[PDB]
Every structure is written in C-alpha cells, then in structure tokens.
Amino acid sequence: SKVTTVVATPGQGPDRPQEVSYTDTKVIGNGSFGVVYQAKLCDSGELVAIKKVLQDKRFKNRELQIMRKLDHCNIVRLRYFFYSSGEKKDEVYLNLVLDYVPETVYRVARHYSRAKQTLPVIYVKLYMYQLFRSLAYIHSFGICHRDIKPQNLLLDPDTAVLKLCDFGSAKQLVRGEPNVSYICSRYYRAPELIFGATDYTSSIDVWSAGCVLAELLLGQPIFPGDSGVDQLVEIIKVLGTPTREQIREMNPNYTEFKFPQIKAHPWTKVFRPRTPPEAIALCSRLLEYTPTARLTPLEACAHSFFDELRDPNVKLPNGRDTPALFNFTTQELSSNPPLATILIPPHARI
Ligand SMILES: CS(=O)(=O)Nc1ccc(CCNC(=O)c2ccc(O)c3nc(-c4ccc(Cl)cc4Cl)[nH]c23)cc1
C-alpha cells in the first residue's frame, strides 16, 4: 500500500494548495471518460474516488470549473483536485478527489433487469425526485449536464441518497450562441439533439431524465437503437409521429421531412399493466417533442407522483429516515418560488 502523497487544491476553499496523501488506491472504473479510482485518505481514513482525466493544458478544464462552483447535497462533492502524469509530450492528468458513492441507477437497473422484476415505485420516487432536484440546482446556474443517464446517477444503498456525477460533457449554455452538436449519449439523447439542434435549452436534461424514469418502469431502455436516425425511428413508434408543427418548434432547418407516419399507442399501453397513474403521467409531461413543453426540474419535483415523499410518514425501506428531501435553497426555487408551498410540506424546517 503505497501512501501516495500529492499537492492538492481544495475544490471548495479558495486556491491554496496543501499536501494531501492517500492509499488503497484501486481502479473501479475505466473507459469513455475517466479512470475513476478508489482510495482511503491517510487522514480522515475516509473513502474517496479519484477521477483521472487528461488535462487540456493549452486550455482550461471545463469539468473542473463547473465542478468547483457546485455544492448541492445531491451532487457528488469535490473534495480536492491535483495533477498527475505519464510521458511522451507530457500530457498532464487532472485528478478530481470526490465523495465515494457505491452502486448507481445503472448497476441497480441492470440488477432487477436480470431478475425479471423491477425497482419498487417507492425507490423510483426517491431516486428520480432526488435527480430532478439536482437538475433544478445546476440548471438554475445555466449549467447543463447534457448527459443525464442511469450511469451517472450515483446512489448510496443504505441511504437511498442519489448524487449526480460525471460533469464531463456538461457545459454552461449561454443564450444567443449556437452550441455545435456533439454531446449526451445513445439511449438518452433528446429529439432536437438527433435533429442536430443548436439553440437547445437545458430542457434536454429533462428529456434524458425522462427516459431514465421510463426505463425504470419497463426494465429496458425505451428508445433503443444504435443509430441516431434509426433511434428516432423508435422514439416515434412510442410517442408518435412528430408534426411539422413540432419539428418546427424543435428548431431544425428540416424544411423537409419523411418519416414513419405511425399512429401512437397510448402511454397506458407502453408501460406494464401495473404502472401507477401518476408515474405514467409524470413521464408523459417529461417525454415530449416540444422542448419548451416539458416539465422544468422544479415542477417535476412537485409532480403528484412524489407526494408520497411529502407525506409525514414516508417509511424508508432501509429502516432509517429518508434523505433530506426538502431543504430547498432559494437558488433551486429560483425558477418558480411559489412552488415552495408544494415542495416544502407543512411539517418541514431547515
Ligand atoms: C458501459 S457504461 O457503464 O455505460 N460506462 C460508464 C458510464 C458512467 C460511469 C460513472 C462516472 N463515474 C464517476 O464520475 C464517479 C465519481 C465519484 C464516485 O464516488 C464514483 N463511484 C463510481 C462507481 C461506483 C460503482 C461501480 Cl461498480 C463503478 C463506478 Cl465507475 N463512479 C464514480 C462509469 C462507466
């Protein structure tokens, strides 16, 4: 166990490096983006996750920045950050020291998925509500995850506390500037995004969150497809054919069009015979073609589907009480304060 000692900068305080050392270093994730390690901090003896990434060098790392601003109880925390290396031309490697969380909605989904069962609705609420709330947070700052997917929804089992991770493909959408295109993922990219948009809002994250809720309600991605265009061929078969009235609102210079003129089969039949009325409705007001027609994270939190969480007797399947689900800050209420008369129930404080 080599006690690796480095120079780190508190992603929380100002900018004043102090020696931090760790150990137990063990890889736990490698791929598309990052080489997420796992380690014990020689001091607190705590658990953490080091997210090793290539440091642009000639430019400023966006992930590190967006990460330093944040500080929401439902978004993996940035403890420290330090640099590493390799060789050749000496590409620098940025190290993000973060809060170690175990499972994920992904690993959790792939589990009930091979048990022909499904995530009990009460858990779905706790996970989704907590996700939508984190969204409500970053978005209030104009930041867009642009990659809300089951894989980046970390979740601590014995707490049912979901923290959003991987802010790599996340950028701050500013109005009056076209964003190219490249981003998000396969099963969780939005329609406008497949129609190659460029003036798309944060509403895209709502669409990715929308899917995840649909997937958790079916035990399989709702809009499969490995090919973008082929994917839409599937979205339509579910939601229905997108009118010029819609394709227009989606923004596209698609002055033309020619796709599967299929007549949709109601959300009451897409979801298994048991899906409760509201979890279906919430999904309907989530998965819509018109970007400016979808629920806003804040409103999503206040969808009837999460009432059970606003009930004085919310019994947590684990035993101990449910996560701090109401400490809404003025910032998260930013988009529509009035909804505080719904989000913070009559028995809440702090
Ligand atoms: C094939 S895939 O699964 O679609 N690819 C893929 C997509 C997204 C991610 C999450 C990004 N990771 C973090 O930032 C990240 C950040 C802070 C953590 O404390 C932490 N703990 C994990 C993790 C836990 C359990 C297991 Cl079994 C595996 C991992 Cl990696 N990831 C993280 C990992 C892999």
Image (spheres, rainbow, N blue to C red):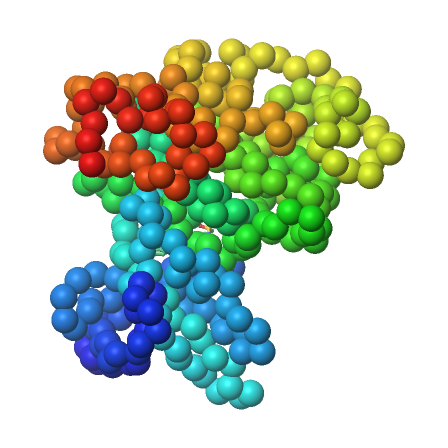
Q: Which of 108 and 310 is in front in this view?
A: 310
Q: In this view, does 25 lie to the left or right of 63?
A: left
In the rendered view, does 320 fall on the left or right side of 213?
Answer: left
Task: Judge left or right: residue 203 versus residue 227.
Answer: left
User: Residue, x 64% and y 47% (percent of image)?
Assistant: 175
User: If the image is split into quadrants, where does the C terminus sit?
Assistant: top left
Q: Is residue 106 visible?
A: no
Quarter of the rendering containing residue 300: top left
How many numbered marks appear? Answer: 0
Residue 69 visible, this angle: yes
Q: In this view, which residue lies farthest toward the bottom? A: 88
Left or right: 63 with respect to 193?
A: left
Give the x, y percent position of residue 124: 35, 28
- Residue 318's place in the image compared with 19, above or below, is above
Residue in view at x 45 percent, y 26 percent: 299
The residue lying at 23 percent from left, 41 percent from top is 157
Q: Give x and y (percent) for residue 117.
A: 35, 25
Q: Is residue 165 above or below residue 317?
A: below
The residue at 19%/40% (across/down) is 158
| Residue 183: % across, % down | 60, 51
Quarter of the render that holds ligand 1: bottom left
Looking at the rendered image, the quarter that the N terminus falls into is: bottom left
Q: Nearer the viewer, residue 332 or 85?
A: 332
The image shows residue 323 at horizontal and vertical percentages of 22, 36
